[PDB]
Amino acid sequence: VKVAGITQDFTDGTTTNTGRGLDVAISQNGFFRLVDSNGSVFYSRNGQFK
Amino acid sequence: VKVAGITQDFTDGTTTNTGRGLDVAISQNGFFRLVDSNGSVFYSRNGQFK
Amino acid sequence: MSFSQAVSGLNAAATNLDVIGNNIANSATYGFKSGTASFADMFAGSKVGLG
Amino acid sequence: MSFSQAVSGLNAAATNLDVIGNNIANSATYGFKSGTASFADMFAGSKVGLG
């Protein structure tokens, strides 16, 4: 035997209020897309920003 | 945390009536000067004297 | 998870206490229109609500 | 690395408590602004993470 599989459960997180105008919470499907200095492209749900 | 400070505030003291000819109050920021038992230079805000 | 529901409910209760406290505090001030607050739950989208 | 994530998560919990503690102790510091820190897993892309 061996284990081989990738899976993520995309249920909406238990949503909490924080008041700051740079705390952004997602619902439903997907991620929003970020870019790095070297031009790399990525999708994340991390909602805290500056 | 550190705690470092004690301060005695110098806001008003409501001035009240007693009638003794040697009772005094200092309106505004003044003080009295005293020597101690042998000279130590002291200052005081107490208003009673005989 | 009702942990989030309960913490959110405590935040809501505290805010309601704050607003009622402010109504009382300026109670005597002329022209002081009184304030109210409103409550809601965030889309549930599950078996859970969210609080 | 399970042991590594165990120790580092314990330290992360300690850090969260310690931001709590410096907040609480300073709650009497006039005008003081409270703090918070962010968490992340060394998600090397493998399954989910490594620590």
Image (cartoon, coloured by chain):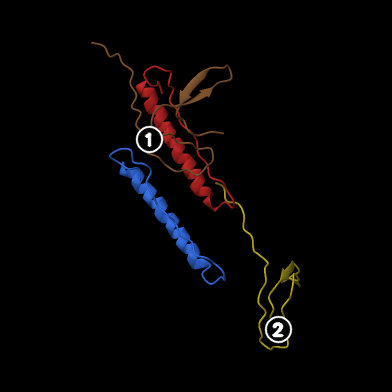
Chain colours: A brown, B yellow, C blue, D red
Q: Up-down: is D10 above or below D48?
A: below
In front of the other: label 1 or label 2?
A: 1
Q: Which residue is mark 1?
A: A13
Q: Are marks 1 and 2 on the same chain?
A: no
Q: Which residue is mark 2?
A: B23
Q: Chain of mark 1?
A: A
Packing grade of label 1 (10 A; few <14, some 14-19, many >=20) is few
User: The N terminus of chain D is located in which quarter?
Assistant: top left
Q: Nearer the viewer, residue D15 or C46?
A: C46
User: The C terminus of chain D is located in which quarter?
Assistant: top left
Q: Residue at x 51, y 19 (%)?
A: A41
| Number of callouts | 2
Type of amino acid under label 1:
Gly
Q: What distance separates the C-alpha of mark 1 from that of mark 2? A: 73 Å
Q: Nearer the viewer, residue A5 or B2?
A: A5
Hey, which quadrant is residue B45 in on the image?
Answer: bottom right
Type of amino acid under label 2:
Asp
Label 1 residue SS = loop
Q: Relative to B7, is D23 on the left or the right?
A: left
Q: Nearer the viewer, residue D23 or A4?
A: A4
Label 2 residue SS = loop
- Which x, y percent locates residue C1? 31, 41
